[PDB]
Length: 186
Ligand SMILES: N[C@@H](CCS)C(=O)O
Ligand SMILES: [Fe+3]
Figure 1 (spheres, rainbow, N blue to C red):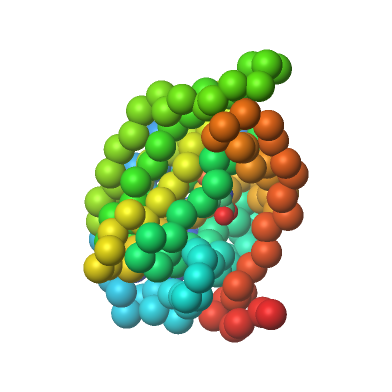
Figure 2: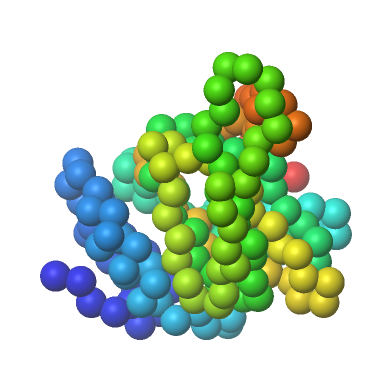
């Protein structure tokens, strides 16, 4: 029985319930993530920016089955084209806008990766992806507004691949946390 999260803290408790079992109900998780109305005061602690690239800020370690983090995107900051390591990825906008560009898994042959589609995620919207769906790139294309997003991954993962848009070639990346629980972690 899914209720509206009243606050970020509330959202986290609900996520522990949802992941209390071995199976994820994706539409339910996406629904509750969406239902949370972004309140900048609730997550300001986690919203730590870097001048040159986007940052990953851990919010909750989950119950072994997931974790939850906040990503902060300066003007013009974006990601690589990437996968999600056989895990669920949920992404919700907390501030600003992000452009999400979808790509298919590349064939063996070296080829331009052509955009399958793109969309603009606006404040409070929650997107979902997993490897069965495809790959994506996420970008703050604004010249004037920073962006902030909330990401839920299940199971947790700290590695993934980046794909070269010219060739489809992948490289394994290890991701780092800019902060954990509000604390900068160099
Ligand atoms: N999964 C990547 C990009 C956002 S979905 C990350 O953790 O930085
Ligand atoms: Fe992603």
